[PDB]
Structures are given as C-alpha cells and as structure tokens.
Amino acid sequence: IIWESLSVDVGSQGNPGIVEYKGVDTKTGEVLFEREPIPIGTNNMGEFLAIVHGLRYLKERNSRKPIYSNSQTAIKWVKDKKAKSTLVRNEETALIWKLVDEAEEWLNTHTYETPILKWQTDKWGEIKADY
RNA sequence: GACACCGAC
DNA sequence: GAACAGGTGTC
Ligand SMILES: [Cl-]
Ligand code: NA
C-alpha cells in the first residue's frame, strides 16, 4: 500500500440511483472532499467522477500523490478519457451525464502525472473511501 | 463465463 | 456487527 495517497469511492442508494462520492487521505481516513448527491447515476459513473475530481483536487494543490480507486471500470474510462456508460440519456439522467461529459472535457484539456492505482480489495480489505 | 464494483439474527 | 436478488462494467 502506498499510504501517501488519496483514496476515492462512490456511494449510492440504488444502482442506478442516487450517487455521491468522496475522497479521503488513505493513511488517516480524513475526508478531503465529498460531492453532493446526484439524483440518478450509476456506480461506475460515480467512480469515474470521483477519480477525475481527485485529479483536479491534487493538481490544484500541486500534489504528486497517487489516487487509489477500487474500480477497474472507472480506471479504464479515465485512461481512455471516455466513460462508456450504458445509462440512458433522459431528463432524469441529464445531470450526471453533464458532469460526466464535463469530466471528460477536463481530461481532454489538462495534463497530469498522477498515478491512478487499483485498490486491491481482495488483499487489503475495503478501500478507505468506502461508504 | 471470469473478474472488478455498486436493495432487501 | 453477521447470515437472497438485483444492476453496472471489463476481459
Ligand atoms: Cl492531477
Ligand atoms: Na474496496
């Protein structure tokens, strides 16, 4: 474990359903950011937004710490700069799809060296940002 | 299919 | 705390 890191995760009520996410200091569990709930989204959209918010957070603070995510899906989406969600686009899902499109747009207009690391839940237990 | 992840004593 | 039925994604 790279203890000098940011861990991020989604939490939801329903999937699809109400989605939020947070970022914590891996060593302490201190909460560094938390997103206001978004009324309908998916687990994987939330995981993606959490990583990209973490990138933005660390870049603004000139931090070189890595990010841990437990999401193989979201780590791939970030590497690709494309969130390949199945969630239908409708008036109910407009909000989350706007956030996702904006996060992709951030990735296409900024650089980062931040390592995005898979949290190994099977070895290490739940990620520290788990709800 | 395998894997990573997220309502109801 | 501990003991069936879902969706969202990749490989
Ligand atoms: Cl960054
Ligand atoms: Na985890």
Image (cartoon, coloured by chain):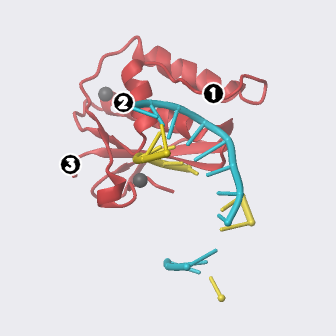
Chain colours: A red, B yellow, C cyan
Q: Residues within 10 Å of mark 3 (few under 14, many from 20)?
A: few
* Residue at x 36% of width, y 23% of height: A79
Give the image location of residue A76, x and y in percent: 40, 28
Which is nearer the eye, A63 or A46? A46
Which is nearer the eye, A72 or A68? A72
The label nearer to you, 3 versus 1, is 1
Q: Quadrant of residue A86?
A: top right
Q: Pointer 1: what residue?
A: A86
SS type, badge 3: loop
Give the image location of residue C3, x and y in percent: 55, 79
Q: What's the amino acid at mark 2?
A: Leu
Pick whichever of labels 2 and 1 is earlier in the sequence: 2
* Residue at x 29% of width, y 39% of height: A117
Residue A69 higher or lower than A45, as above or below:
below
Q: What's the amino acid at mark 1?
A: Thr
SS type, badge 2: helix
Q: Residues within 10 Å of mark 1 (few under 14, many from 20)?
A: few
Tell me, for residue A55, which label it has, or none.
2
Whether residue A29 appears in this view of the structure is: yes
Q: Are marks 2 and 3 in contact (CB under 8 Å)?
A: no
Is the CB–ligand 1 distance for label 2 below 8 Å? Answer: yes
Distance, label 3 to label 1, CA atoms, is 33 Å
Pick whichever of labels 3 and 1 is earlier in the sequence: 3
Q: Residue furthest top?
A: A109
Tell me, for residue A2, which label it has, or none.
3
Pick whichever of labels 2 and 3 is earlier in the sequence: 3
Q: What's the amino acid at mark 3?
A: Ile
Q: Are marks 2 and 1 in contact (CB under 8 Å)?
A: no
Q: Residues within 10 Å of mark 2 (few under 14, many from 20)?
A: many
Whether residue A51 appears in this view of the structure is: no
Residue A14 higher or lower than A75, as above or below:
below
* Residue at x 61% of width, y 49% of height: A12
